[PDB]
């Protein structure tokens, strides 16, 4: 309506201010980068090239890389042809930035730019060494679901990092990743029954109980029935002999209706029968159900 | 009953404060009134974060309909005159939360606060922008009673020589623009163009709000990136 009428004039005025106030004004620099993504989406090659050059100039600048990373991703989403050949500059800048390790904005730029199939093949290695962060995991999971180009490669990289992480609070994130979404496993669940038996941290135990039930998805051969019945025993004992009810409450909540055919064993029943006579009601209510 | 409450309030005022407020809200709901009011008055008089948190914690739990609204109205105006530190932002949020309870006097309190905030519109303009945004967020219907004077006042306060003042003005203007768009475009465009022809971040912030409101396609991507 009104904004759509005086849009080219605003875009021309916005471009002039960015081109002129290049090194004269951090308040304007933060505002200019934010205004560029709004202009790029609303007004879509001279404008795109100038915006990319201004973003590239501010990408290496201090206190502007995070703003420029989001601005570049927004422009790439608006037009895939505009950032088709200009994406390599972002990849090259982040190629040695990840190996060197501020990194939160690097993952966001990749996630925004992701939404062709050969650039992600080698880019996984620099992201793997960047660090174990929820943003990195969320961005990688989003890429796999939206674009499952090499599902095994993303699975292999995530599995390799998870295996070495648990070999020796930061580990709790790796345990979350395996129990977050599907993976491609009897060796993990056997060692998974060791963290809550030795680690005195209450926080790691809260996630430890949650991941055991979700990782037990293979539930007529006498090779997996024995192991699944063993890992079930550890959680049942922990859910009644733990000091604080917070760990106990999540143990029985994980044992939902699905385990009806696995909780009917006589040895397992005695574990549940104790939970009826519990000091706190929140566990008694769950136990009786 | 009162000694423990008084001790908890002092400890929270001076994660400990959040835990005390949650415990006090649970204890108040489970369950004297004069002792709580006296402790809150002493905390408000003296510290600042604890008194506002205790008042906010008791808001929506004890069940004050009109009696608590009047007492909180006087306290809310006491901290409105002077823009105290970042802790005072909770007090404005507490006032907005109390004004959103749905009381009979809430409509009159919102109108009185809006008129007072218009006069203020940097210990006055910045506080008014946050207060106006809090009122708009809590009571969008009550914020539409006087929107023409707000636009004129915002167009003059955003031109002041400040940095963080325009940040609250842009957010307050965006909230007013969002409410209007949910249910002035010419005035906003003309005012921005006049100021476009210190005056760098403010002009871009006003233009950014108009661009986001006009086209929401890019806003979804920003929200998705922030969530992930």
Image (cartoon, rainbow, N blue to C red):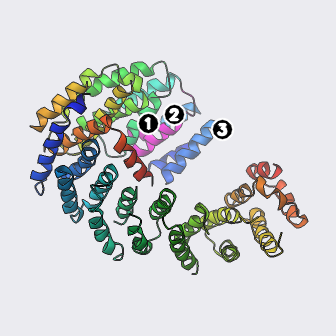
Could you say which is closer to the camera, residue A129 or residue B67? A129
Could you say which is closer to the camera, residue A67 or residue A3? A3
Specify the label residue B59 is tagged with. Answer: 2
Q: Residue at x 77, y 50 (%)?
A: A286
Decide which of tag 3 and tag 2 comes sooner along the chain.
Answer: 3
Label 1: few (<14), some or many (≥20) within 10 Å?
many
Q: Tell me whether the residue at label 2 lies in contact with that at label 1, contact meaning CB atoms closer than 8 angstroms.
A: yes
Could you say which is closer to the camera, residue B188 or residue B80? B188
Report whether mark 3 lies on the same chain as mark 2.
Answer: yes
Callout 2: chain: B
Q: Label 3: which residue?
A: B30
Residue A243 appears left or right of A127 = right
Q: How many marks?
A: 3
Residue A185, given in percent of the width and then of the height, sits at 67, 73
Decide which of tag 3 and tag 1 comes sooner along the chain.
Answer: 3
Decide which of tag 2 and tag 1 comes sooner along the chain.
Answer: 2
> Distance from label 3 to label 2 (Cα)?
15 Å
Q: In which quarter of the view is residue B133 placed? A: top left
Callout 1: chain: B
Q: Residue at x 82, y 62 (%)?
A: A262
Looking at the image, is A97 positioned above or below residue A138?
A: below
Q: Label 1: which residue?
A: B94
In the rendered image, residue A232 lying in the magenta stretch gets the answer no
Residue A84, given in percent of the width and then of the height, sits at 30, 59
Looking at the image, is B34 positioned above or below residue B48?
A: above
Q: Secondary structure at mark 3?
A: helix
> What is the span of residues highlighted in magenta in the rendered image?
B42-64
Q: Residue at x 43, y 31 (%)?
A: B138
> Distance from label 3 to label 1 (Cα)?
22 Å
In the rendered image, residue B58 lying in the magenta stretch gets the answer yes
> Distance from label 2 to label 1 (Cα)?
8 Å
């Amino acid at each position: 309506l009104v904004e759509s009428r005086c849009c080219r004039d605003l875009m021309e005025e916005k471009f002039d201010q960015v081109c002129q106030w290049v090194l004269k004004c951090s308040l304007i620099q933060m505002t200019i980068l934010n205004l560029l993504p709004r202009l790029a989406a609303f007004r879509p090659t001279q404008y795109l090239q100038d915006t990319m050059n201004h973003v590239l100039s501010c990408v290496k600048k201090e206190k502007e890389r995070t703003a420029a990373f989001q601005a570049l991703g927004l422009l790439s989403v608006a037009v895939r042809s505009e950032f088709k050949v200009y994406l390599p500059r972002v990849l090259d800048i982040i190629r040695a930035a990840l190996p060197p390790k501020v990194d939160a904005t690097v993952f966001t730029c990749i996630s925004m730019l992701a939404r062709i199939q050969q650039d992600i093949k080698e880019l996984l290695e620099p992201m793997l060494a960047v660090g174990l962060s929820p943003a990195l995991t969320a961005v990688l999971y989003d890429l796999s679901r939206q674009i499952p180009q090499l599902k095994k490669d993303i699975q292999d990289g995530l599995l390799k990092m998870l295996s070495l992480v648990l070999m020796h609070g930061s580990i709790t994130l790796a345990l979350r990743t395996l129990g977050s979404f599907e993976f491609e496993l009897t060796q993990f669940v056997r060692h998974c029954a060791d963290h809550f038996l030795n680690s005195e941290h209450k926080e790691i135990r809260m996630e430890a109980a949650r991941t055991c039930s979700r990782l037990l998805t293979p539930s007529v051969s006498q090779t997996a029935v024995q192991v699944v019945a063993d890992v079930l025993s550890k959680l049942l004992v922990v859910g009644i002999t733990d000091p604080d009810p917070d760990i106990r409450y999540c143990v029985l909540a994980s044992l939902d209706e699905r385990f009806d055919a696995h909780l009917a064993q006589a040895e397992n029943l005695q574990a549940l029968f104790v939970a009826l006579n519990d000091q706190v009601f929140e566990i008694r209510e769950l136990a009786i159900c | 009953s009162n000694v423990s409450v008084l001790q908890q309030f002092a400890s929270g005022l001076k994660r400990a404060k959040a835990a005390k407020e949650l415990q006090h809200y649970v204890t108040m709901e489970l369950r004297s009134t004069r002792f709580y009011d006296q402790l809150n008055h002493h905390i408000f008089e003296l510290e600042r974060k604890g008194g506002i948190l205790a008042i906010a914690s008791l808001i929506g739990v004890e069940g004050g309909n009109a009696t608590r609204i009047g007492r909180f109205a006087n306290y809310l105006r006491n901290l409105l005159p002077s823009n105290d530190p970042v802790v005072m932002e909770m007090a404005s949020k507490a006032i907005g939360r109390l004004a959103m309870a749905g009381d009979t006097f809430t409509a009159e309190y919102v109108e009185f606060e809006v008129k007072r905030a218009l006069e203020w519109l940097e210990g006055r303009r910045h506080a008014a922008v946050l207060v106006l945004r809090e009122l708009a967020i809590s009571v969008p219907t009550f914020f539409f009673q006087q929107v023409q004077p707000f636009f004129d006042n915002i167009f003059v306060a955003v031109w002041d020589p400040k940095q963080a003042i325009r940040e609250g003005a842009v957010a307050a203007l965006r909230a007013c623009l969002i409410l209007t768009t949910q249910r002035w475009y010419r005035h906003t465009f003309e005012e921005a163009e006049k100021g476009f022809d210190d005056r760098i971040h403010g002009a871009l912030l006003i233009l950014n709000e108009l661009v986001r409101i006009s086209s929401m396609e890019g806003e979804r991507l920003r929200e998705e990136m922030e969530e992930i």
